Amino acid sequence: TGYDRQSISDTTAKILLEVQAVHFNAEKPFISGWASPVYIDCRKLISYPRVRRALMEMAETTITRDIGFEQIDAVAGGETAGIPFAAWIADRMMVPMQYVRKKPKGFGRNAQIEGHLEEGSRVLLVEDLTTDSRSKINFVNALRTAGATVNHCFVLFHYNIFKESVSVLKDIDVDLHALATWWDVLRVAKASGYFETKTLDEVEKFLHAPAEWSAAHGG
Amino acid sequence: TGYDRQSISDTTAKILLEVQAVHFNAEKPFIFTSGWASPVYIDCRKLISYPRVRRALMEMAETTITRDIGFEQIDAVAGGETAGIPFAAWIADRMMVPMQYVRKKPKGFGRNAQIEGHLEEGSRVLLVEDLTTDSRSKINFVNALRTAGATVNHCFVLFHYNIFKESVSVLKDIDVDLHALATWWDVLRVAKASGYFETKTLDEVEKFLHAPAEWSAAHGGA
Amino acid sequence: TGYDRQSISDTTAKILLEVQAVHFNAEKPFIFSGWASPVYIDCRKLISYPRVRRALMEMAETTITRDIGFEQIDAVAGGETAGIPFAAWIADRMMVPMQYVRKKPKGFGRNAQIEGHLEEGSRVLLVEDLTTDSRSKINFVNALRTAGATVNHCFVLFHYNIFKESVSVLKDIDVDLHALATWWDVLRVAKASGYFETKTLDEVEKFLHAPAEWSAAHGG
Amino acid sequence: TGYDRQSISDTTAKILLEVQAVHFNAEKPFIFSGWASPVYIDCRKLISYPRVRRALMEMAETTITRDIGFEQIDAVAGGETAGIPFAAWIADRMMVPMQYVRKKPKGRNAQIEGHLEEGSRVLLVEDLTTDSRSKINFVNALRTAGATVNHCFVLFHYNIFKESVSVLKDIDVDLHALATWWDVLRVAKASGYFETKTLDEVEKFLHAPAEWSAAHGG
Amino acid sequence: TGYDRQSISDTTAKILLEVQAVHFNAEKPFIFSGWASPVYIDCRKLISYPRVRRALMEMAETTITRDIGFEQIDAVAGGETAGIPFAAWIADRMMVPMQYVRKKPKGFGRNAQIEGHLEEGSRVLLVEDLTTDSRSKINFVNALRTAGATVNHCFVLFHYNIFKESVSVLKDIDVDLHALATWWDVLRVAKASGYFETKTLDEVEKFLHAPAEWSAAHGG
Amino acid sequence: TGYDRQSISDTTAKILLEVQAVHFNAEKPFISGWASPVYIDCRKLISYPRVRRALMEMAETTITRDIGFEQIDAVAGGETAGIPFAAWIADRMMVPMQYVRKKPKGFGRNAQIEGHLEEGSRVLLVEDLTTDSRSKINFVNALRTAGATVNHCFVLFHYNIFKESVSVLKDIDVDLHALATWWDVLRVAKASGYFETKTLDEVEKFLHAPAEWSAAHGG
């Protein structure tokens, strides 16, 4: 459902707002602390068939356009949230699928990885969303310990409100690819006109300075 | 795909033996984490790394579901955590139905803590897992789905051990039917027919299958 | 979805009984026209179920390819109202042009009863939801033949059977009748399932063996 | 198959003109109940071409998802013998149940063939719209059976009559179309396969339909 | 399309006889290098029929998966202008890289006879339209093995199965031959159909049982 | 993976450079004489599944947009070169397939054509690539001898550096449709930045004057 980056992001934002995977609440923030007015549950997108089909089509388009057609030999999912999306992407791309556990279960170079992973394979990490890309280090290092070549990471949603969201993965030579960001959702919601002005202003203030807003509203 | 139980089972056994998802070792039995000793090891998670194998497995899964259960008797597909999520996703894609997945432990307030994804009240849900041994871990997931309002009467597994007496009755006591593509007997029969395995190993496997607990106690150690 | 004639009929009967497209009631027969029967079928309900209709279309394509042939049909024509969805799906599966025939003419030309484009000499397969005595099929067959199409085959999802002329009327005008299931298949599958009482199935069997006598005895 | 609205309309007009589903005749107007018109559209010819219908159904799905939403439709109900094939193809693409509505009742669910769950959201699919007067009956028939009808889809929209849209908005039904007569006129003018006089007469008709029909006989 | 070997063979024979890719003529034998024969097969006609070639590809994939295995082939290599379309379709269905082998080398190097990228150690399946004595397959097998490919299987839509060394010549170099139908299957289906005269089918049977003697007796 | 002509051409150029079907060498020109700094092997394209799927989608889009949806009744391919692409296009278009031999084998109308060709059929000629379209004359005449109507020709790559590459086909009333040209590959390579400036300048001066460059560099 899109061709260029902007259309893909707009379609992703519309999909997220339509299935109510994105929630806004400025009066009662969503609190592990970190009170925020925005809540996202990308795991609801697996319960809507047309939505997930469109999202996977756009995911394949993004992977082909930004990475390459013959640069990925396997698709590895996250712990439990990115496994369905990884499975669908692997089926579309006709590549082997693996998934990486959060904690090792056993001894060896393939303890964290479930599935068959050939030596030297080029693996693409796929999970639902990122906030700081700090949970990405464990999975990338687990895949690299087993011999895979991890240089690209795909996620449905990217917060893009923290400075080290993309620099952390770049320092370990991993590129972050995302279908949409919080700014795209904010722009689509502002254009739609179904949200009150005060709520959108509060959301914009939070997205500009996340830590300051969180600390000053119950963090 | 065979469109009948025997052909589906034989094809699944050949698939498992070809990709070496099933291992036989009688000289050095597989001592598991719980101390159980068995000469047979199966890793259904390896099947997701082979495109054609997984495609055929999902086609046979859809055929089994539509034959044993029915075409319009399932409203959603739920997968157990980690192991069965890819198979649940593929089955949901083939069946054009919503997909959810059940966590092993609750994380949330209630009535939706153990289930990730939207679940409409009164929806008939099919539980998909990679394999079952005694079907006592499936009760937790079935109760989690029923707590959210889903009506669970069927559970699908790629592999069913079928070597424990209460493998199916434990689910049937809570009104859940167990459907599977292949059993250990099917794999043993196909391995015997193939002839790539020595007679002693297959005899040991047959002895274990006929008496699991005694074999675990004696030949490998409790 | 099956691969053999016996497997297709059993699967179709199970599909019909599962989605309740077939109803049995011997205590209060379905008095249609004055005809009285203990059986009722509504093949139009099969289009409201995605998986059921997909399976039925797969079996329809399999039956067409096995009985008629892979390259013997150049267009798929559906009857008025009822058979148009099935004709559309079969044409999509077979990658052939689709037409549909109105019950009554809408003009004065040769292509008055046909809504579509029909090239001269095209071999056309006529698709309908069900047939009872195939007396209404002659109108559609003659309408297609007036346009120049060559009609030698007709496909129906459900064949009522019972009546002896149901295939002879079409065979007299060189049209072969193909079907997925009959009433006998549905009755056999219902008896095997065990969800229906013995008295009801006995009444249905008596009706199937003697339709006119049963209608006269239990109604008009 | 295009992506944006303009591309979809342009290639839909190209498809209509290529399969000759659109006819222009200024010298001898088409007497339809009179109403002499120089333009003729036969959208039922579109089902006899496989590639054309595949492209059109892809564009229909794209338009439905883009303008209505991905999960706003639970059933697709066509007209009677006009848009039933298009409704079937759209329902198959959308993985959504199909129904269809008759012109006249036969026997709540007397006018609807198929299973229609109460409270379901139903999309009307028809071959074309002229004044959207015949769609009132189908929308009311579906709403009698409990369905929620808020969107109507048609392959071709005349867009030359003022009430062709507002009559559906009065009953809270949105009209979605793949192409209009203006798109066909623009594509025909750009192609250059039509004489200038014919296109000028067609444009004059499209600006004032009733006056042109009355002047030329009707 | 079928599910077992016998069903696949029968369906393929019906397909070949329906599209007239197989011709029978005992009065005027097909003399082609001499070698008069009453049978003629043109497997290159099957690419001009969409449904026929789609069904043939389904059956080809089923045979490959059933006999060889799901994960035992890494590339599909066609012959020279004859099996290239079939190889392309099989590779698309199997989601594997495709190559094709020239009849004669064009250049110098290990990859002189092979067009397309072939990774070292790849297990390659050779696809052709038909084998008469499989003497020409040795050249393609050796060309593929020169570039590092491991060739242990060869798939063909049709296999004559009337020469003793049809399968042994490939088996001597560790290549297994798989086919959808043989001349015996076509003869059996033609006899069952009844569209062919008894004398013609008797002559074909005599030729199939002893091809060299029949050719010597009827010319060539 | 494209919508318009420009996007399709750019994606085709990226595909060709990614799988290394396009080679640049200014210091040592390749090679019947005609030393050139550019080498293209479109037959490598059939060994990559995702690449060939994307290229066939683009081919179908181009054929439908430029020729028409119902203007082609058969697809014929050149011998040994465009047969796989013709097969994939025919499968996509649910249209019969034929292929034309370079040299006739037999006598009578259909001696040079393999497959079933109905009289009056509209046939699209498919080839891997064309340089001067001199070899397409034989195939077009062979198809027209059998009764086919040939008015369109499709090639994945078009050199577009010779003046008669399109006029020679237009003289016999045949149109040439292509996915990419050498200019578009050059533009994509220049934008990518993976090639040295001297090599790209030499390639550009070759593509401007091919014959002069070949004569000057020992051709």
Image (spheres, coloured by chain):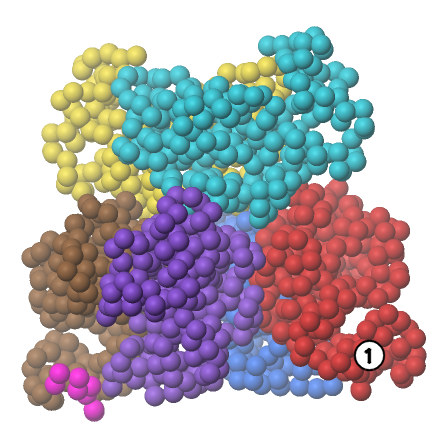
Chain colours: A red, B blue, C brown, D purple, E yellow, F cyan
Q: Is residue C8 above or below residue A24?
A: above
Q: Helix, strand, or loop for circle 1?
A: helix
On the picture, is C36 further left or further right than A164?
Answer: left
Please report the bounds of the magenta region as a residue range.
Answer: C27-34
Q: Position of residue C60 (x, y in %)?
A: 31, 59
Nearest the camera: F116 or B127?
Answer: F116
Q: Position of residue D93 (x, y in %)?
A: 46, 62
Q: Is residue B99 visible?
A: no
The residue positioned farthest toward the bottom in the image shown: C27
Quadrant of the image for the N terminus of chain C? Answer: bottom left
On the picture, is A155 further left or further right than D204?
Answer: right
Q: Is residue C67 above or below residue D209?
A: above
Q: Position of residue E72 (x, y in %)?
A: 56, 40
Q: Residue at x 69, y 58 (%)?
A: A6
Which residue is identified by label 1? A202
Q: Is residue E64 magenta?
A: no
Q: Residue at x 54, y 27 (%)?
A: F129
On the picture, is F8 further left or further right than D183?
Answer: right
Q: Chain of mark 1?
A: A
Q: Position of residue D18 (x, y in %)?
A: 38, 48
Q: Residue at x 29, y 65 (%)?
A: D215
